[PDB]
Amino acid sequence: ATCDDGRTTANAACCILFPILDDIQENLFDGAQCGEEVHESLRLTFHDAIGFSPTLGGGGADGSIIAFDTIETNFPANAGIDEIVSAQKPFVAKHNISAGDFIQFAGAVGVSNCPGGVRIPFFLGRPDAVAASPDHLVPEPFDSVDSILARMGDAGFSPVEVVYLLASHSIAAADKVDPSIPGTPFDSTPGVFDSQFFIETQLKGRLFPGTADNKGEAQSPLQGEIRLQSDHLLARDPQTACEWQSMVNNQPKIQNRFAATMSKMALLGQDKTKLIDCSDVIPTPPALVGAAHLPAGFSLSDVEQACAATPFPAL
Ligand code: HEM
Ligand SMILES: [Ca+2]
Ligand SMILES: [Ca+2]
Image 1 (spheres, rainbow, N blue to C red):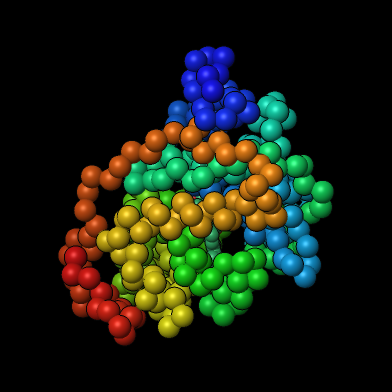
Image 2: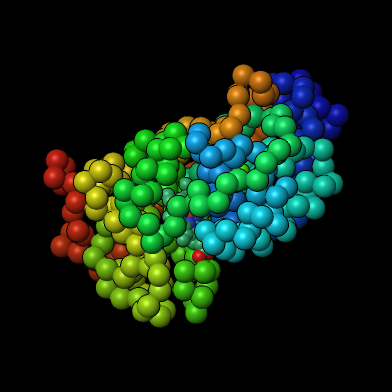
């Protein structure tokens, strides 16, 4: 199909996304930058989608975190999410797509701004949300590995798929974990979708980048980085450690698995056979140019190797 402005897309129904794409690149992502707004929007895709439990309800990736923001932003695991919900809401009001479609579309567009990034498959047509997420369905950085895996598994993700989705922490920072140092990133390259997150979480903890007493926070290996206790444990737990290490210096796997697993997450509560594929509207991401590395001055002896089957790669 050819849209009114001449841009093309496989299905014609997708044409309505082009003006929306232009508006968000300019007015949500500050000129298509891989910065805080993109990171916030990616976090939002998960906080929307994970509100899905076979036994309790919730419609998964349904826009409920916006439609029922009064409720969902009261949940403690949603701290800080009000900021991005309030930023996205006017876009949903102005354009003619559901909040559930918008949240996933904005997340996919955002990721495409980041070097190393992928185009997450995107489907159009989610109905408006009809119920708020149940309470207590979002994992916290102070939850055990068993608790996190049980929650994610309840929503349909295997332990390896949890590791794949956590590639998101390669373009990510924390504001609430330690409020004395807001915007401290989870890896040394928060504006690059790369394997540095999987590398740097494997390093021995050395210090706290801000204050020392924060719930859900582990020692960081670097002054300019923060570490979640959940990522600390996941990198080391027999259930996840080998898959974690397998992502290191393995950008093709990070790309493939993140795109596929993000699509699955984006479709929680939905049926792709009743939606329209509009994946080709997402921009083409830049590629990486620099190689994966330990931080300068660090060596293998600084790595806490946790995979009995396979030694940590020599970087
Ligand atoms: C698996 C369990 C997870 C836990 C325990 C967890 C925990 C956290 C925490 C504590 C923060 C920082 C919030 C703050 O203090 O500002 C954060 C940020 C973030 N999360 Fe995760 N998360 C998990 C999974 C995911 C998944 C599956 C995604 C995929 C979209 C994701 C995407 C992000 C992003 C992109 C940020 C950075 C937000 C920003 O810089 O504004 N997280 N996460
Ligand atoms: Ca939801
Ligand atoms: Ca990174």
